[PDB]
Image (cartoon, rainbow, N blue to C red):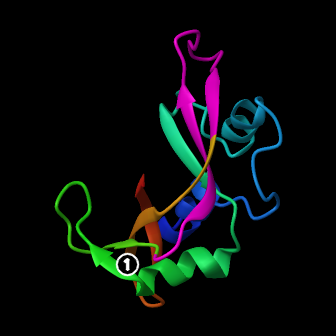
Amino acid sequence: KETAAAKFERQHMDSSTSAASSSNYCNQMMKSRNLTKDRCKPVNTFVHESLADVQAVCSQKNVACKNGQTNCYQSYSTMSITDCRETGSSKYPNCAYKTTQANKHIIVACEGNPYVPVHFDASV
């Protein structure tokens, strides 16, 4: 169940806001995107740009993925993102996340035809 493309969208797309609204943004979003169901996903980034703009990164700067895969791409421009990271007070099933707002390049791995993001590698 769940294509890689749809999983990327579920984990990493939030085009409904221009930026994280409150310090509770990550706690709410990690839960509601089902990333705290069987485990506290330790780290996860949301992108506040249109899906088209994020898909377009698959046609931007070809770079190495962190594991050495050759199908990663860095956005030419910076993007509004929110980094969500599990904090010291976090213990499944009571997950607790630090919310970190930022504007930076995203790096994604792309696959398929249509060639779309299937993994969030990093931000810089």
Instruction: Give amino acid for label 1.
Output: Glu
> Callout 1: few (<14), some (14-19), or many (20+) C-alpha neighbours within 10 Å?
some
Residue 51 in which image quadrant: bottom right
- The residues colored magenta run 76-100
Task: Give how far across and how far down residue 58 sits, in percent.
Answer: 43, 81
Q: Count how many numbered circles sit on residues in the image.
A: 1
102 horizontally vs 26: left or right: left
Element on which disc 1 rests:
strand
Q: Which residue is pictured at 62% across the width and 21% down the height?
A: 95
User: Would you place residue 112 above or below residue 98 in this image?
Assistant: below
Is 40 placed left or right of 120 in the picture?
A: right
Asked whether residue 107 is drawn in magenta, I would say: no
Residue at point 64% right, 82% down? 52
Quarter of the image that includes the C terminus: bottom left
Q: Position of residue 93 (x, y in %)?
A: 62, 17
- Residue 95, compared with residue 28, is above or below; it is above
Relative placement, left or right, of 84 versus 68 is right
Residue drawn 41% across the image and 64% down it: 107
Q: Position of residue 53 (x, y in %)?
A: 62, 79
State yes or no: residue 99 in magenta: yes
To which quarter of the image does residue 87 belong?
Answer: top right
- The residue carrying mark 1 is 111
Residue 68 can be seen, yes or no: yes
**Quarter of the figure with residue 37:** top right
Q: Nearer the viewer, residue 39 or 98?
A: 98
Taking 63 as reference, is 7 above or below it?
Answer: above
Q: Nearer the viewer, residue 49 or 116?
A: 49
Q: Let me know if residue 40 appears in the view.
A: no
Q: Residue at x 62, y 26 (%)?
A: 97
Residue 108 picture location, percent across and down: 41, 66
